[PDB]
Amino acid sequence: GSSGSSGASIYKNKKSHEQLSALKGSFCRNQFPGQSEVEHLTKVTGLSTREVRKWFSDRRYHCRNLKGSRSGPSSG
């Protein structure tokens, strides 16, 4: 029972906001998807389960160590 396939290489392709927006609506609320979220998106976008989950990775990457304007809200 293996899930994490072998060969995780960031890709690049043209997408239609129409679908993009949907995906986001899931992230903004929940950091990372689980089982239900995906099942839904996969239908809201049609993209393969792998494609749907993959995206999430992108958004995160794009927004990494992007601090400066704020002071730094620690976890406490």
Image (spheres, rainbow, N blue to C red):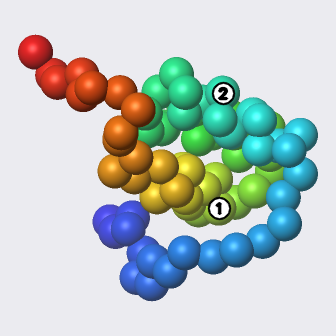
Residue position marked by numbered label 2 in the rendering = 25
Q: Earlier in the sequence, mark 1 or mark 2?
A: 2
Residue at far bottom of view? 7
Rounded to the nearest whole Å, what is the CA distance between mark 1 and mark 2? Answer: 16 Å
Q: Quadrant of residue 55?
A: bottom right
Furthest residue to the left? 76
Residue sticking out furthest to the top: 76
Q: Position of residue 70 (x, y in %)?
A: 35, 27
Relative image position of residue 12 (x, y in whole percent): 70, 74
Labels 1, 2: front one: 2
Name the image quarter holding the C terminus: top left
Q: Which residue is mark 1?
A: 51
Residue 25 point in image, percent of width and height: 66, 27
For the residues labelled 1 and 2, say whether their Cβ atoms are less than 8 Å apart: no
The amino acid at mark 1 is: Glu
Describe the element under mark 2 as helix, strand or loop: helix
Residue 60 appears in the rendering: no
Residue type indicated by callout 2: Gly
Quarter occupied by residue 31: top left
Q: Position of residue 9 (x, y in %)?
A: 50, 80
Quarter in which the N terminus is drawn: bottom left
Q: Residue at x 24, y 28 (%)?
A: 72
Left or right of 26 in this view: 45: right
Residue 37 appearing in the image: yes
Instruction: Please give left or right for residue 50 compared with residue 12 in the image.
Output: left
Measuring 34% from the left and 50% from the top, which residue is drawn there? 65
User: Measured along the vertical axis of the image, is residue 34 above or below residue 48?
Assistant: above
